Image (spheres, coloured by chain):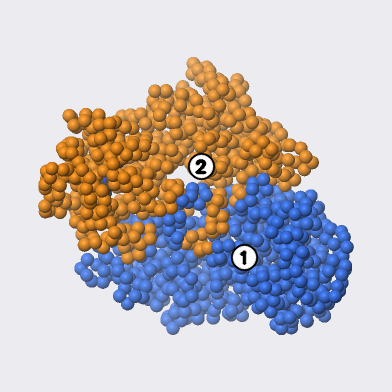
Chain colours: A blue, B orange
Amino acid sequence: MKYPVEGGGNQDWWPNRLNLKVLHQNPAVADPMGAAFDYAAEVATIDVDALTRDIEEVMTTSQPWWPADYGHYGPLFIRMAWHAAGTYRIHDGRGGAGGGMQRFAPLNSWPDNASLDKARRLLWPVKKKYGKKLSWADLIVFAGNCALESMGFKTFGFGFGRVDQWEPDEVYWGKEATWLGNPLAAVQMGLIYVNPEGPNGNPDPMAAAVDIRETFRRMAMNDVETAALIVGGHTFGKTHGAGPADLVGPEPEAAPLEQMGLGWKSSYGTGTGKDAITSGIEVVWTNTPTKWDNSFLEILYGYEWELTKSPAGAWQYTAKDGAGAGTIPDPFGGPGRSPTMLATDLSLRVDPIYERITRRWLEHPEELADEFAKAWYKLIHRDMGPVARYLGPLVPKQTLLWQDPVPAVSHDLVGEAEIASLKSQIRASGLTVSQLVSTAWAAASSFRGSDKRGGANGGRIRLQPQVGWEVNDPDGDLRKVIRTLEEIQESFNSAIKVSFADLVVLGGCAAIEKAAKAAGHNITVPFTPGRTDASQEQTDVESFAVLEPKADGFRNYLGKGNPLPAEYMLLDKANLLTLSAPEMTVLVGGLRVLGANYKRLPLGVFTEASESLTNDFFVNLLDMGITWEPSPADDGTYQGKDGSGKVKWTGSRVDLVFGSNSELRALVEVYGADDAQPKFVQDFVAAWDKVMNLDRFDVR
Amino acid sequence: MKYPVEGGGNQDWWPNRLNLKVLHQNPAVADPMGAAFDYAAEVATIDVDALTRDIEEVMTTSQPWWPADYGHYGPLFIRMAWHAAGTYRIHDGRGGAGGGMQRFAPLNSWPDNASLDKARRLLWPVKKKYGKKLSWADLIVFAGNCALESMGFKTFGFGFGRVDQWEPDEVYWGKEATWLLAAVQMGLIYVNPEGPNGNPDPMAAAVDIRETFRRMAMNDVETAALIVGGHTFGKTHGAGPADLVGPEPEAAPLEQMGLGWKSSYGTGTGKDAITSGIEVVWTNTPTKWDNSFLEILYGYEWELTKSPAGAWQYTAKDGAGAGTIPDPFGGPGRSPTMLATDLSLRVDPIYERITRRWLEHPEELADEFAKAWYKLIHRDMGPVARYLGPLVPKQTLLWQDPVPAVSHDLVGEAEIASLKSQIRASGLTVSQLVSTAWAAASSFRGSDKRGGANGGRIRLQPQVGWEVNDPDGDLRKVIRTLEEIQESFNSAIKVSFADLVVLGGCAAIEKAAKAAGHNITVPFTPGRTDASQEQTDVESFAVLEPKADGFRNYLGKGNPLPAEYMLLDKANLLTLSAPEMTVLVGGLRVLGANYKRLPLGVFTEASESLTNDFFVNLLDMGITWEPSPADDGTYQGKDGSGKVKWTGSRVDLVFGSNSELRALVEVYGADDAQPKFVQDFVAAWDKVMNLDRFDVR
Ligand code: HEM
Ligand code: HEM
């Protein structure tokens, strides 16, 4: 229907086709830094003092193509930071500022990130003067933070380490196929949090409060943070509004080329500064919108508000009787204005929940500072991962209970001879292979490569938020495996201290070695030590209530509330784990033949003899002498009807896909060859070593 | 609108968004074999003597879930190769057999490749026995070529080498959004069998076939070789009206394991399957070679009747031939039948002569069909240095872009410096050397690997006269100076011509780098030869003429899109990637490599000096842009005070507009990256100049 370079390919002929482009996004070819570049080794060598001494400079020179309000840019950079790490939705994990996606995406065109392309273009001198030693995400967010600092503040700190990706990330943002139309977080399509004029353009404070709380909750922010975040943020800078909001041009994706990749080039007046239009509201919040103080709340409790319209054609509030008419300084010189407020932010005065936590902030005006610093530092470094990546000399030392704190190694890391000793001690009185893998896999499947939260490290697999997960059948034998592993741990220690997660991954390794040896290959899985155990008080039970996978194909289990059919979720779960197209298929075959099945069902297994790591899943799948017909009980299962009329195999919806979707058919059509056995077991161990070492960030 | 794993973003909100996901396609991540796996090295060990002894067996055994007419699959295989090497489009170069795209693509769902999805399954007991030492594409077109030989025929040869791919390539097949360029009806690989556009008249079928095949290099005499030589084998499954067939494979319920067209009529297979909806049985012995097709084609006079499937097919009048055709599964014989496209060869005046001439002695038909089939198969492989295996018919050909054998003593870099010296110590300027070299290595298409810098065709008639290489400019001067150097060098180990072309290009890059302060050594691998004017035909090169070489900022007439896209579609052929594309475009813009001396695009104040000044001067926001008052697709870089300082084109400012490429320009446009930029430019350049060097890699 249209050319490929414009769109094209397939998907113009099929609406819902299993698109295999999401597995290998962000390839190593489109990386202009090269194939041997380590960002963690470079970003530590910048002189953050010199950088801090430079961003402070770019925040004072009013560039002539976009004038500076009050001769300072700080507000704009804080807004940039907030709209850069305000997309992080915990329901799946994708988004956030961990990829700096605000540059190129549907993000750099949402009808709220308007007048933000100019904000990024402002920072070009600093990135130009530094080069490859400053990834764009780090520059944006740290510029916001250093602005907040420069405008009079004492921040909690900051840490570099976010890496850039050079291709847009595909994330589901909303069913509404038009701007302003459960896995979501922005109540509109294109909004970040809330329609500034109240939900659905309706300026009601109560609905605004309900909605703003129901939105922030999908980003793990409490009730005290939300109030702190909003207040501390909007105590800075002004709005942008002039004539009718319909005069703005197109967005920086359908804009003409002479605009150098900008947008919203307003034709009204000179087009910038005193007449620039962006959100269609015209409000100044404080009375000195360029430096910090406890004044926004005073205005929040200083005048009684009544609704009005906007000179730009929008809804807002304004003090009655002309109170304070002409008391707030002009953004570019001129007579005073009237103290105004947005629609939502009045909720902080009427809503009874926020009232108890805002009325306290009139007196004790200092507590606002620390709470805002904490909430901000939480909003920033939310998608960086464990503590071991906070590079640079500005990170604090104290840990926070949301960081998933993992205590540092306080003993000698185990040795190699001890590794073989533990192998022998675990494969002689441990348990079957189908158990030592299932528990091990479950300890490394809570990972999410979106924000690198959770995983094998910490050993949380034996604590409350994960043992009770129904996906790891609690009334099964997982607790018995836990008892055995802890007792062999303490026995070897009584016989250099080995932690628990170390031993879990070692059990998985020894089980895979057992299966491979049963298959006829003396192969070894590479194991590196360097994990520690977490305690119940350092792992929040409620925070981890989202990692519980609603659909996990690699163990063949689907739950309830599943958005898409039970097949696509396999790739989705295989996309967070950052698995290439081959490493997903081989891993599926391995887990299927190894008996890593939820409740030990006879689904997925395609072998007459289990616990033997062979390619018997694939060779037996592609056989055409069997006919597949949906099950008679109609439970989303199928039946391997043979040529004799006897049911032979019984796979699930996540299996027969690996023999149907003509693309994924190819990868199987390799590992199922006659001489593929010396390759399968060798390509499998690689993928298994890759999964079990995703959260190993202290050494990689 | 929909989830990413099923549909995606970045497309619904804006349809006309420059999609860079077409550059990184076929990456190094989705490769099961992993990293290296030199396919050109593995297949050198397979026993074609044994592979033939196995495909011969898989054909004679009738599978129980798809019987074989007359107990032989030879037919269904012969077609499979054809529809696997019939997706060639000469006007672009994509498709072809060398992509193995017969599997995962819209290709395996077109309402023409029906029932063929079964054939890919009949071959599994063959590939399973070999695995990685024999890719699909080679196997598909071999089972094609190897079914002919096993059926009373001495073909011309065969060669492996078509390394497969692991993701569906992106190709434009047409504008219609419904089934039924090069194909005449969307989905139908070639001609709608029931006459062009459903009109059952042979005279129109002939004028359609002529133009259609003319889009795939086949002449007028190599056409009748195929059709007559291709439809001597096998029948056409079409019993029963084409109304009960299942859905297409890409959208079928999974209990079919990716097989499409689950026919509910009758038993569903065998003597009752449905493929295209025509019941026709050509020869009287449809599983061996003989001069039978032409015999029946002239044996009677024809008349149009209806089909048991509801299509228009023909049948001899007079009621003769009652039962003269063997029943495909034992029983009463049908009447002598025929398609609609075949009658063209009886009524069209052009094919009439050759058809009449093939009936006096059919050995000429055998030979012509042999050569035509060989051309139909080994077209998507290009240089003769890629053919592997024993069965290569290494004698010669004329359409293979032939080059003489590397005969003289090569060079051992002891004099390469002197050549790189005399090319500046007795030659021209950098703004001409890089221009002519890049021109001589721009006639390349990583699809079928035709053209290329090899052969030294930059001094021959088909390429010297192209418009994009302005002949009135100075190309002749550069070529004559290079010739004088070559002749002055061999009198004292002889060096060819394209040798000196790319060597002067590299030495000019070195000169420009010295003019910047980075004494960088360009790599160079000798071993290319110059072809003559006779072995370089003119008719097959008229397509390689670039219609929009965005690298050089040249826009011809005949672009379906603006210039901003015709750069990618160009930079997608050369097997480039976004970093290399940006770097190479910047280098060619700053080194003065436009098809004139135009200052259009140059963003420097001291040319002929390789540097990143283009990138850094592009991004400065203090410079505003607006369309020039000439309204000739040129923008006017207006400075802040009202003066003209830069003049760019659509191919330039796209790097300032499109957000993805903006990141790359940001990277190379720093200040501690000029060494990185010049080094990566040298690397990408040596990648371009060494695309067709297949005799070494
Ligand atoms: C949570 C609800 C929020 C709403 C409804 C909201 C809405 C808005 C609106 C309508 C504007 C004016 C846009 C324009 O002038 O074009 C704005 C700007 C701004 N926002 Fe937000 N925002 C929210 C959250 C935040 C947060 C979390 C922060 C900081 C942590 C923040 C900091 C700012 C600042 C400093 C500006 C001033 C921009 C300038 O001076 O140019 N806002 N916000
Ligand atoms: C204008 C060119 C062509 C037309 C109109 C045409 C038409 C057709 C049609 C409609 C079928 C029915 C498919 C089926 O029943 O499975 C068919 C089958 C077949 N075609 Fe073609 N085709 C063309 C080119 C070729 C070429 C170039 C070859 C060989 C080099 C070829 C060889 C065959 C064979 C052997 C079959 C029988 C397959 C079987 O019996 O399993 N055709 N042709």
Residue at left offset 55%, top offset 63%:
A177
**Left or right, residue B228 beside residue A502:** left
x and y percentages locating residue A245 in the rendered image: 71, 60
Residue at left offset 48%, top offset 62%:
B5
Do the residues under discs 1 and 2 have CB atoms within 8 angstroms?
no
Q: Nearer the viewer, residue B25 or B83?
A: B83
Q: Are marks 1 and 2 on the same chain?
A: no
Bin the neighbour count of mark 2 within 10 Å (Cα to Cα): few under 14, some 14-19, many 20 and up: few
Residue at the spot of label 1:
A180
- Give the residue type at disc 2: Pro
Residue at the spot of label 2:
B560
- Give the residue type at disc 1: Leu
Residue at left offset 38%, top offset 60%:
B251
Which numbered tag is attached to residue A115? none
Q: Nearer the viewer, residue B396 or A535?
A: B396
Does residue B385 show up?
no
**Chain letter, disc 2 residue:** B
**Chain letter, disc 1 residue:** A
Does residue B6 show up?
yes
Q: Nearer the viewer, residue B308 or A492?
A: B308
Q: Quarter of the image holding residue B46?
A: top left
Query: Which secondary structure lies at badge 1?
Result: loop
Q: Quarter of the image holding residue A432?
A: bottom left
x and y percentages locating residue A667 in the rendered image: 39, 56
x and y percentages locating residue B552 in the rendered image: 58, 35
Q: Quarter of the image holding residue A389?
A: bottom right
Determine whether A638 is above or below B594 in the image: below
